[PDB]
Image 1: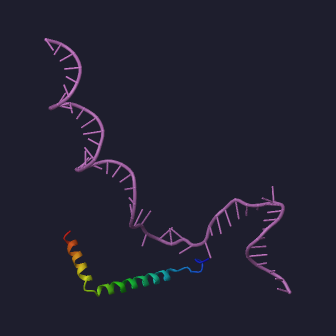
Image 2: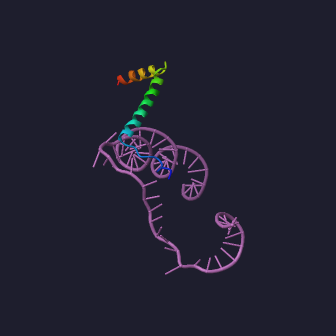
Length: 52
DNA sequence: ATTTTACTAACTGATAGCGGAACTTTGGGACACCCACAGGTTACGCGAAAATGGC
């Protein structure tokens, strides 16, 4: 009963919801990027990675 | 002089530890599309007490 009350999606609906998820994740990523501690961490991770 | 015994040292087994490689074990992943379930059942009967319905 509780599940049936939700309508089924279509292709356009699935793409729209996925786009909203990606948009939210992008906003979160932009928020984390505006942080003095974030970018140096990624830079040092790449520094260790490129050293194999 | 001889026999029994106490002392001591060497052998051996059990055992705790370790190495390491094989073996078991755990967690992650898989992109044509798939989109609401069972699921046997019951020929009981009787009395109480508890929950519903009638105006």
